[PDB]
């Protein structure tokens, strides 16, 4: 209810309505990203993450401003801070996304197939992210 505690002071009764929009209005990605960096990459939990308010329009945009902020956490004991994000680098498309490979991405291991595949995919959005950076 911290959000409910935050939304309450955020304005009276109509706040419950603005609670749903303002939830993802800022970050549906950084929210995911920090969470994806926090513990779990599971899309089902990601659904259950935003299912606590009010469909896939949240997970649709999850593919671009999104990918950027996830790369802004890179900072031995912090060696996995890269790994946790490094695993978030492998995972991508709807085929690979919609399935339990989302929980298998963190199993990295990394296929030699993708090694040339996502390099094409990151280079697709490599320019867009800097358009957000710059």
Image: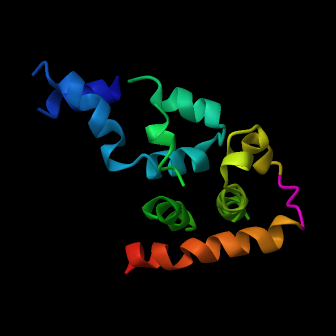
Q: Is residue 106 visible?
A: no
Task: Please tell me which residue is depicted at 15% across the width and 30% down the height of the picture.
Answer: 9
Task: Please tell me which residue is depicted at 47% across the width and 58% down the height of the picture.
Answer: 66
Majority secondary structure of the magenta segment? loop
Residue 41, percent from left and from top: 65, 43
Q: Splitting the image into 4 quarters, where does residue 75 fall?
A: bottom right
Q: Nearer the viewer, residue 77 or 12?
A: 12
Q: Residue furthest left?
A: 12
Residue 27, percent from left and from top: 39, 49
Residue 73 vs 127, above or below: the answer is: above
| The stretch drawn in magenta includes residue 134 | no
Does 28 sit left or right of 14 as displayed? right
Task: Please tell me which residue is depicted at 16% across the width and 34% down the height of the picture.
Answer: 10
- Which span of residues is magenta-colored? 108-112
Q: Is residue 13 visible?
A: yes
Task: Please tell me which residue is depicted at 64% across the width and 59% down the height of the picture.
Answer: 85
**Quadrant for the C terminus in the image:** bottom left
Q: Splitting the image into 4 quarters, where does residue 103 fall?
A: top right
Residue 7 vs 27, above or below: the answer is: above
């Amino acid at each position: 209810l911290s959000e409910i505690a935050k939304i309450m002071c955020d304005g009276t009764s109509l706040i419950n309505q603005m609670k749903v929009n303002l939830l993802k209005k800022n970050s549906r990605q950084i929210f995911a990203v920090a969470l994806v960096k926090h513990g779990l990459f599971s899309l089902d939990i990601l659904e259950t993450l935003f299912l606590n308010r009010a469909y896939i329009t949240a997970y649709l945009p999850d593919y671009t401003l999104a990918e950027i902020t996830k790369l802004y956490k890179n900072s031995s004991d912090s060696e996995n801070a890269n790994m946790i994000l490094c695993s978030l680098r492998f995972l991508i498309t709807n085929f690979e996304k919609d399935k339990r490979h989302g929980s298998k991405y963190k199993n990295i291991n990394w296929t030699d197939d993708q090694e040339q595949a996502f390099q094409k995919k990151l280079q697709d959005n490599i320019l867009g992210i800097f358009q957000v950076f710059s």
